Length: 311
Length: 311
Length: 5
Length: 5
Ligand SMILES: *NC(=O)CSP(=O)(O)OP(=O)(O)OP(=O)(O)OC[C@H]1O[C@@H](n2cnc3c(N)ncnc32)[C@H](O)[C@@H]1O
Ligand SMILES: *NC(=O)CSP(=O)(O)OP(=O)(O)OP(=O)(O)OC[C@H]1O[C@@H](n2cnc3c(N)ncnc32)[C@H](O)[C@@H]1O
Ligand SMILES: [Cl-]
Ligand SMILES: [Cl-]
Image (cartoon, rainbow over all chains, first blue to last red; front, side):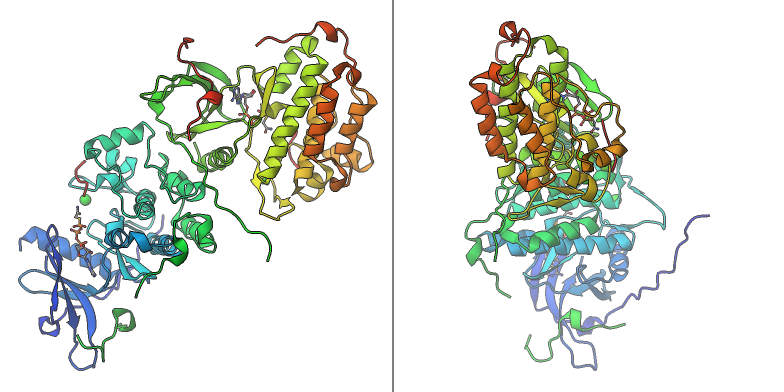
């Protein structure tokens, strides 16, 4: 026979609603609402900065729970950590607060301060996260700059596991059936046959990097989603970002090969960008890159989730 | 400290498959297939004669891309120009069409028409190309008559960068690890220690000239590749070509010295052969050399790649 | 943000 | 065309 499955002994923590203090809304629209607050577990003198997602039909609940399932099953420095859920009117996901929001907005808001060093290391960090995810045998299916959070300019993590799927021990791919999926970030295979693999996540990684290298530009801006499949088949791809050397662009391009197994592996990606991070200005030619720097309820018993390690 | 590295801002053009018109196959075998066609970029009224290499495993792709990387990084009148690549099933390299093929086949096909003037100038041209390559700090590792294309009998260029390697600012040599390499064209150092330098490219230049002077004869014809290393160590070298004066043979011989730094520099080679080109019949004694001459979709908006200078 | 296939 | 070392 072939390889089997091991038990998933992840713990799903259920939190007391009277332990939060929704300090202020962080954002809402097409996903429900995301507030900002503190989690203050009875007893222990600890105040944890958190994000509360209060996304009331059965479909919504069944979906936000599928998400918590994934988040509760992964543990890595570059993957957003789930603190637990709250079972009230509608299920609330509680996660570590990322003070600077999603990377897409962050680079758009600080175009004039993103140096090559930060960019390349973000690339390394995202690759480490995804590489980890591949070990767990999990296909994210929605990697994009908007789904990468910023704890600090020096530390980012992958988030939004609402489309993630966990493959079997020797399963090579996931066959989706239907529904809205972000076309401009998906691999040709995914668009044409609804096939998802770690390698199609690699294609999404290429687009994420591009977004970052273009300081937040929109992929195929203006081009209708329905035309994307054509363009790709014809061989066209996203343009070489102005600050990129052929070295970096080459990595992106390999991520967009028609042949999935030809694209690079996250482990290789981590290696490539690490090397480049050792001599940043040699791979990204950014104006004023020499002088670009990025910054960093009651501060007392406040502890970041990364230092509150409950079993 | 020592010298550093500068950014490589070469642009890698990705072409629309619907912009070519593969007119007919040019050749195939141990490298994939090479068709002949036109490139017709949307808009501009331009038809460019091109060569399409359609060489589908990950190894193949990873290798043809390494090649495009080099080609996209060099720009010189005597180095084949890369127009871009096409990302379809398997990566296609698009290059300027050289109507008369590789020099080896060309001299074999026109033995009875190769005059001393053409030969010597080809020698000058190849040296200029390689000298250029040395400035870029690039070791070709596979110079040979078969890897020199003919745009016209008066203009040749170096091609096939599948083994090329780009050295560091002050790196003196490249240490290969293994794999098939053309023994009869490599320097003793390369065979014994897998060391490659501009100087070992000079040894290959010597053999290329010999091939040309012998009108296409095979180096060490008959002798097994495995014996070559012995012969060389013993001091033996390729024979003096019938049409060669001791002057020309002497240059070849210097290219085959055991001591790499003793061999001539391409810049010197260019000078030597230039002088000789001014009085051809004095260095190459060819029969009937006085009467030897060499010749030269819809002709309308057809423009050779050398006149289509995209940024 | 790009949807549908 | 000559190979191996
Ligand atoms: N087409 C689509 O799938 C919707 S696009 P989207 O609106 O970017 O993604 P969506 O999944 O709908 O929402 P998500 O919850 O991923 O993000 C909503 C906003 O809230 C901020 N956010 C999310 N988690 C955060 C944490 N942990 N800390 C601070 N801020 C957080 C995001 O920046 C986003 O703008
Ligand atoms: N031992 C070996 O490395 C293989 S020997 P080879 O078969 O001579 O070299 P290889 O690298 O396998 O093939 P390459 O693509 O270099 O040449 C194949 C044939 O196609 C013709 N060719 C190549 N580029 C051309 C351009 N740009 N224009 C016209 N014709 C071209 C060559 O003449 C060669 O015969
Ligand atoms: Cl789905
Ligand atoms: Cl090699």
